[PDB]
Each structure stands twice: as C-alpha cells, then as structure tokens.
Length: 113
Image (tube, rainbow, N blue to C red; front, side, top):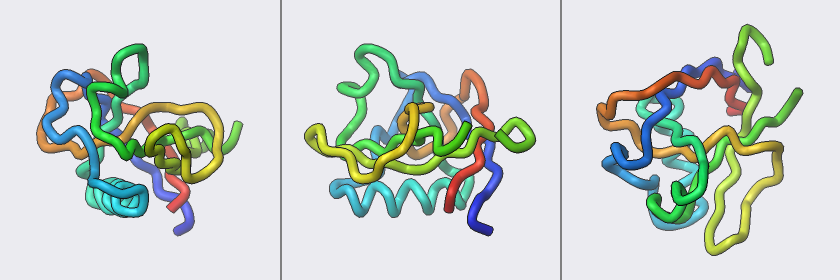
C-alpha cells in the first residue's frame, strides 16, 4: 500500500530517551520509515524550545493534503543546519524513536510510504 494508517504516541520532549534517528539526512529518513513500519516511532509537538532539545538531523511529519477515517495524510521532510529535504505542508511534529516513554496523546496519520 502507498499509504499506511498509523496512531503515533505523542511524547513530551523532556521524556524522550533517544532524541533522533541518526547522523545524516538519508539515515534519519531511513530510520524514521523503519520505526514507523515497526510501530516504534513517537511524535513530539514542536513549540518554542523543543527542537534545540532534540538531535539534528530532524525528521518532521508534514500535512500532505486537506483526512480519511480521522487520519491526516502526512509525509516525511528532514532538516539539517536549516536546509529541508522534501517540500510539504504544515508540521504536525518531529519524529523520534519510541522506547517505552508514556505518551500524553495519540496522533492518527495516514503515512505516504
């Protein structure tokens, strides 16, 4: 399937134990996609002071369309030293590995895979 219905655990930035997916744009996009498939991906909602607490390169989920079965359609865009790899809509948050952190909420997304 070109799209996959996922429910992403929303984590508080100060709870996150593994603050990024790796060390290159290509690696973080790779790792994010693997963790999304494996159900081991969390979401941090971006506000003032969140991103400096996480590791670059960043992986964002961004709205790709204006929402089947409650699931917002999203795609992945990476960022490193202020350059983005991909072009998409509004940021829903930054993806991080999920290693058992207790979420505050769930974000239903339809991921362009």
